[PDB]
Amino acid sequence: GAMGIRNSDSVKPTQQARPTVIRWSEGGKEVFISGSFNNWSTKIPLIKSHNDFVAILDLPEGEHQYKFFVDGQWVHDPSEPVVTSQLGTINNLIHVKKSDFEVFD
Image 1 (cartoon, rainbow, N blue to C red):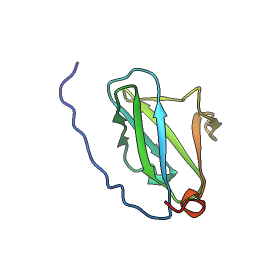
Image 2: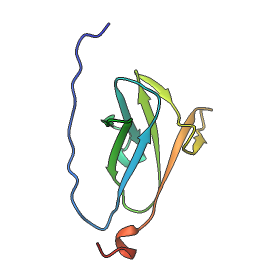
Image 3: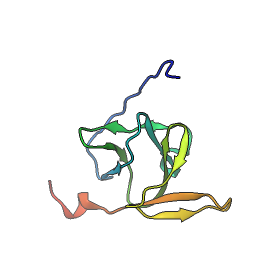
């Protein structure tokens, strides 16, 4: 039952906080991402590539949580690390390293 679907946008400036990119593999039509990096407020749309889905967020440096959203359903990636919430729900964990510091360009 495909009625109607929309999309959003996002800015990708250049600063110390290196951007966090995440790849998704499954073969879905609409994929999103949400974690502690966005206060789990809304679901950011995963930029669909020629190979698979990918999303480039803007994180500082350290450790942040996140979760995939496909077909209005929660799913985890076997290639990426998964965690366990207090509600026995499987989640995803992502880490960011200060590359802007070590790298000059």
